[PDB]
Each structure stands twice: as C-alpha cells, then as structure tokens.
Amino acid sequence: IWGCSGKLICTTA
C-alpha cells in the first residue's frame, strides 16, 4: 500500500 503518512520507512520497491 503506497502510502507515506508519517513513516521514516516508507520505501518499498
């Protein structure tokens, strides 16, 4: 779920 809402670790490739 591509959703960066308050997340240092929101890189998922």
Image (cartoon, rainbow, N blue to C red):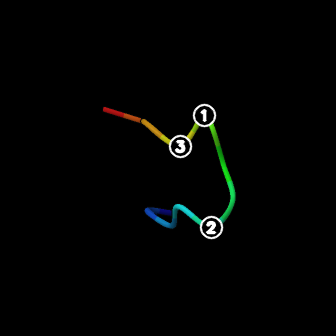
Tag 2 residue: 5
Farthest residue to the right: give it. 6
Residue 2 x, y percent position in the rendering = 43, 62
Q: Determine the image quadrant of residue 5.
A: bottom right
Judge from the rendering whether residue 3 lies leftward or rightward of residue 6; answer left or right: left
Residue 8 x, y percent position in the rendering = 63, 37
Q: Are the two marked residues, 3 and 2, in contact with CB atoms closer than 8 angstroms?
A: yes
Return the mark for residue 9.
1
13 and 8: which is toward the camera: 8
Q: Are the two marked residues, 3 and 1, in contact with CB atoms closer than 8 angstroms?
A: yes
Residue drawn 30% across the image and 32% down it = 13
Return the mark for residue 10.
3
Q: Please tell me whether residue 2 is drawn above or below residue 11 in the rendered image.
A: below
**Residue type for callout 1:** Ile
7 and 12: which is toward the camera: 7
Residue 3 x, y percent position in the rendering = 51, 67
**Residue type for callout 2:** Ser
The first of marks 3 and 2 along the sequence is 2
Return the mark for residue 1.
none
